[PDB]
Length: 190
Image (cartoon, rainbow, N blue to C red; front, side):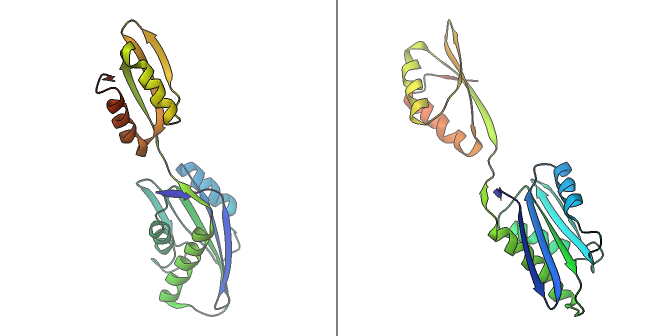
């Protein structure tokens, strides 16, 4: 999954209605509601929104016909493979009715455009690994760590060196395989 690397604002007029999409990365529901509260415009016709944080998601039509604003925004977030993102779409009615179909395309479309234009970065979960290395294998492990640009907490004991490492979840498997290979399996995973 990708998340936003900065906040973005994108405005577009559709059949005279003014749509302003404001998006930001959010790592907790507290942050999502804080962002929405700060960016909502009280005198707008509607402040539709949606956000996704892992399994947690939320969407709101704020008065628009049910299913025409909130879900389309959430679908735009999901369609671009984003997570830990909140999107608000402020709307100022301009005198021309868009119709349910047009609303779905407007809210979803403007949210999608804002998300496409925003800078994005991979959403990575940091995880830890710990293992005990016999003294005969320590040299090979330090070389491996250097070779993979990894730094670890080290504890020297009578049975060898205990290493504690933090790294991206997607890289955990590759590292353990590299470790087991460099030491020919002579290590105790903890």
